[PDB]
Image (cartoon, rainbow, N blue to C red; front, side, top):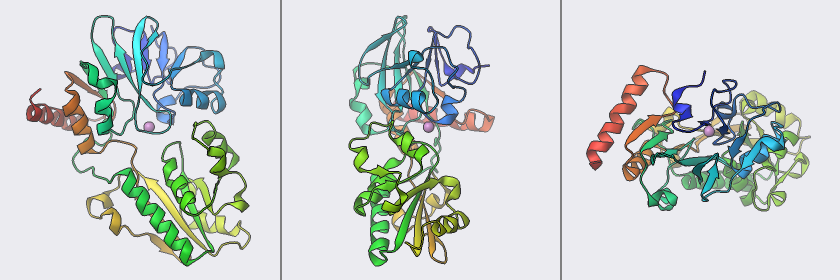
Length: 341
Ligand code: NI
């Protein structure tokens, strides 16, 4: 049975609610993004209307085989009427195709559902500037002050400079980057660009990337591993064992691997600066964990909410324990007393 924080009151709508069977009264199922915890349940046999971005619709059709007649793509930044209710989709600054949804209820209430997002001051100049929000359904993944990490631009600068130095010292080094979902594509695209290479990958991953509307993609990626000196591998292979096994397969072209694991936050963020990060090394293999986040830091979340001034907040992440719920409620009250709403 579908929980309450996935239902939108006064509508026939649900958000990210595909794992509960037929939801009673649901006339339209919204999907914020193509991550498996949020699409869980969708397959080629789904027969109700799905509303989403163009990019998420490309992934539902090609990767999950949902039939075309049940996919309803909407443009961003555009007022649209769905089953008699005005909605707008907004860029969530999460993975490709990820949206927030603004719902204009027939009774006059306005609701924002963030989906998964990385809050940014640019959101303060979207269509959100124009009117008030009564309820905010909020991605609270990192809602605690210990969760700090750098800008995506600082993290990319570290990765490009690290990879360019290594491969200029040793032209026979291979670079490998881990992946297990869409998102974080800038990591491997920026490294391949500084090296003057296409990125090489499995046919399955190539297929996924080809759904993402990235400009000039055909110039940036390939399935011909032998032509490329930046390879993508499943995240589960980014360890000394898996990397050894990969180097064997490269036919003596390479004598060293430098590998990247984009993570979210890790406890070494509570001590070490991006600049000071060092790898784990065994022999001719080095692995860097880099803190490339597509979710709000605590400070970015707090800024967004203090600017929006919602009347009520409903968390959508970390909802399963009393201790988490109580922590989040305390920070929401601090923020409100501090800013005066
Ligand atoms: Ni996500």
